[PDB]
Image (tube, coloured by chain):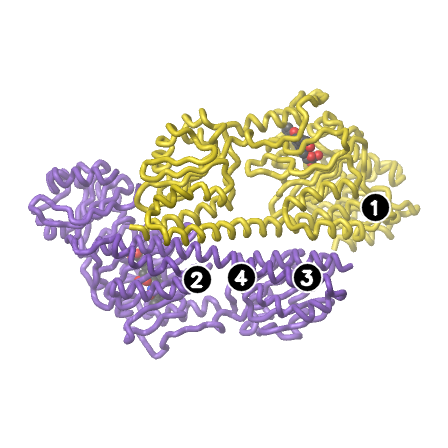
Chain colours: A yellow, B purple
Amino acid sequence: HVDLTNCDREPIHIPGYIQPHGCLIACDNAMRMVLRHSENCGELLGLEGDLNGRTAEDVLGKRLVHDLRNALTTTRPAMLPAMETSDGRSFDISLHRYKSTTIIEFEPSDSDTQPLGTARKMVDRIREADSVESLISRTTRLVKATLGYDRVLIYRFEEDGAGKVVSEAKQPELESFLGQYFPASDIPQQARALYLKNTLRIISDASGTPIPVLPAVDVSGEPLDLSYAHLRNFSPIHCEYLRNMGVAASMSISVIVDDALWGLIVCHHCSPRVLSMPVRIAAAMFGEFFSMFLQVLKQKRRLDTINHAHAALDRFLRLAAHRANLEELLVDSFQDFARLIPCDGVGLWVGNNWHGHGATPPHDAIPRLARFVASVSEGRVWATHALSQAIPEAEIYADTAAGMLAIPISQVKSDYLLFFRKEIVQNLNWAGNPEKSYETGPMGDRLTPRKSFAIWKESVRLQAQPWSEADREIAETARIALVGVAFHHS
Amino acid sequence: HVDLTNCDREPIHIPGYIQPHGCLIACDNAMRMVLRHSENCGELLGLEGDLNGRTAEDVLGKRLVHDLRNALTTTRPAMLPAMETSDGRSFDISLHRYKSTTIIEFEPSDSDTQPLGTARKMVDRIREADSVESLISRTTRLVKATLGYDRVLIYRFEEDGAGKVVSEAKQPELESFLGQYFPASDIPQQARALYLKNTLRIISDASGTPIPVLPAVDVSGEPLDLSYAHLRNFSPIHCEYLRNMGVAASMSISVIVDDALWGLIVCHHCSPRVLSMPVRIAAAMFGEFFSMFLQVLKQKRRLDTINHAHAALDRFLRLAAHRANLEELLVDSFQDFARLIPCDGVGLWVGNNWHGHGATPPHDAIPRLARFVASVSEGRVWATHALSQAIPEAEIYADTAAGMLAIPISQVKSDYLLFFRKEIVQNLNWAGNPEKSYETGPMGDRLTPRKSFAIWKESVRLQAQPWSEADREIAETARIALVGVAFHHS
Ligand SMILES: *C/C=C1/C(=C/C2=NC(=C\c3[nH]c(/C=C4\NC(=O)C(C=C)=C4C)c(C)c3CCC(=O)O)/C(CCC(=O)O)=C2C)NC(=O)C1C
Ligand SMILES: *C/C=C1/C(=C/C2=NC(=C\c3[nH]c(/C=C4\NC(=O)C(C=C)=C4C)c(C)c3CCC(=O)O)/C(CCC(=O)O)=C2C)NC(=O)C1C
């Protein structure tokens, strides 16, 4: 049994079933003996009776088995498009070895597509992108046009595991998910772990009858680990989700940046759809190249951001020299620091006087905040995205200021520069349709995009967009700049 | 007993003695009762008999004890220059609370120096430094001229804990330590931990008679933790070291960068020397400001380095477009990649052909390296500073190439770009005098700069300067640039 109470702990790596668009044979470490096989090995390979106990050379043939052994020579599956069996039948074969068990996946052959050629055309069109936004927007559009899926999304993972739809290409009749968030629980930890091990992940048919593996558990009480198997069957929880959405097929591409799961390129189809091995090889290479280019562009953006901050602080220090009263200069210019760190408001607390700009807490609320900041600051940068978790009184003005970053501007006195952010739900640019409802199944209305979005909204209430490492790094450079020049003027 | 066999595990935080230039009183959490006191409390404060058991108000006076209580209101010692006792005697007082024990340190008062004024003059002269090198070189010279110590050094800690003398200002007659390294064991872990907790550390007299604390251990079997006490006595191992060097006094300033111990500003004097509390306050503030400015300058240098790499790779990709044969371009231009990553040599391994530039392994040795690199690389950047630890055959050419960083330039073929570094002892710029020998003590010749340097040299044999995070980050950006354009040309 699997339900909404235990689906976060579901062992999705050992389902004991495969998808019907191919058949599976498991063999021993040295591919001599057949240990397990899929029920549908009978139909596709055209063999009689049980395969378990019989040798690899007996069941496949000496000719083929020799080539498979040679291909094994670390955990990445070997692709063998268009191999011939004994009778002559052509099959595309995926061969890998994990937990000293050799797995062999067969699907009907397709020799009418060139992987390198398809991939090169796609990678050329993204190679010359000069911004993250430009790469992201063009990629959904490009992948849709090339692989002909009804909908292509890019999800980006937030710090808290939540996913944001940052790009979309779809059929006009389908509803938009652009700007929508899903909760971390919508992709369990064991799913993120598999997504990090396999570039590609295919679901040919959400309504397809799953084929069992024989045996499901062997003599020593072990299940067959299908972590690296492309035929591994999908969770019935995700199955019902796709069925509820009207999605029949899917193919996800993992986006890996600084050896972390940045997000997914995900393709939905409203009818069943299996890509042939050669097309899957091209899509995988594209995914690998998309990941590398995004990594460099993220690196370039970080450098430009912090370079612009250094330039701005130099401009200010040049002014600070020619001007006699530094307090006077800060009062005139504090709003200009909003250019350094993304914020919805910024304020100056100097000589027990408050000056606000943009969305700040109310004038009467500032003294409490100032005294609190002085308490916990200890002459260093202090920052929260959940202001009411620190000061329960702050809940009342969360719609204006739910997040705060404090910069000390004096080594001696308790003067601060306060950056503010509105609660994250305020700044939403959701392009979806609230009138669109979804058909539910046995499990309930939890497995609908509508309910996923409502659960996320509840989780991030009274909270702002978290302060990034780049935000922190700029705040620290501004502290040293202001504390420094404040010391000089005394 | 303490000797060279257990001095790495020495509990230097609980010595049970203090330096004679002040007296110590320990009291209970709420400074009511006197729990411990230094033997010399009798002489300096002019009091009769045992102090333990007597109240704080009885021994110091209601007037003074009130001001001490008020000053406590987290672990940083409170400075109280020129406080009066009962009879009128003037004392400079350092007050702190650690492990729910209040410690009170007394030294004869000095009210003929302004902390802020001294510190401001010093901090002005370093504020406008535009390079790490410029800040480092001027600071030794400046600190010497201001605090009048015979020698000022800056040690910078390497990745392996070793220390390098990166700057020096000294009397002409003294021997130079500039460019010399010391081993990690020369500053134990518990010493680095204390150096990270206290900005300043003073030794008034290496030949001074240490004053015992009474009792050394109390009723419950606890020693007095003097971690934050400026009067805490020094290890006899370090004592003998300074005596062997001809050093009588020392004062070290901790350099803290990204919340790590970057190194020390260290001042040696050949005669005894105690700085008054006001001068120590100025030196501490200077240390704090020196640390902040070095942090920003390190950040600026990292940005400039990686910016210059991006510019260089853009120049190359612009050339790669106009040129038809990419292999031909790489053969002509590979030496130019030496500008990206600091190296003593660079080579190109393309189509099983080798092209070398600078200090590379011999021509006959390259095929072995190439096959090895292909083995462990797995299409990612691979780097070592100890090449012979990976390939014992490589020991023979360590003087030319002891370190290697490999960059794959093809997704498909096993082509690499190899950066090399000579073994670290080759590239030494040691400004010391090998004729200068040192007087040893009971412990042996281990406690001499000569033997410290010889031990370090032995530890880094057959090893190169480690590849930095910045070196790695540039190598990764170059991989994506070369793998990318290599794909386009097919
Ligand atoms: C309690 C367990 C649940 C669960 C498990 C589960 N989710 C998996 C994949 C997956 N889930 C989502 C969520 C969404 N996809 C969308 O397109 C939208 C909205 C438009 C949502 C909210 C996504 C995106 C994915 C990735 C695949 C895809 O997007 O098509 C898996 C994968 C397991 C496997 O590899 O077999 C598991 C398991 N999902 C739940 O919602 C819940 C509650
Ligand atoms: C086995 C234990 C040893 C040891 C312990 C120890 N060292 C400490 C401080 C310290 N040691 C050095 C080493 C040098 N200083 C130099 O100037 C030179 C060469 C020119 C060397 C090699 C240094 C620099 C320092 C810091 C202070 C200073 O430089 O003056 C301490 C401090 C403990 C305390 O806080 O009381 C301990 C303990 N030192 C050894 O050499 C060895 C073997």
Residue pointed to by mark 4: B467
Query: Do the residues at pointers 4 and 3 share their chain?
Result: yes
Q: Could one spot residue A228 in this view of the protein?
A: no
Q: How dense is the environment of label 2, judged by Cα within 10 Å: few (below 14), some, or many (20 and up)? A: some
Q: Position of residue B81 (x, y in %)?
A: 19, 49
Q: Secondary structure at mark 2?
A: loop
Query: Do the residues at pointers 2 and 1 share their chain?
Result: no
What amino acid type should be assigned to the residue bearing mark 1?
Answer: Asp
What amino acid type should be assigned to the residue bearing mark 2?
Answer: Ser
Residue pointed to by mark 2: B131
Which tag, 2 or 4, sits closer to the chain's start?
Answer: 2
> Could you tell me which residue is drawn at 78 percent across and 54 percent down?
A71
Which tag, 4 or 3, sits closer to the chain's start?
Answer: 3
Quadrant of the rendered structure where residue A166 is?
top right
Q: Closest to the observer: B21 or A339?
A: A339
Q: Secondary structure at mark 4?
A: loop
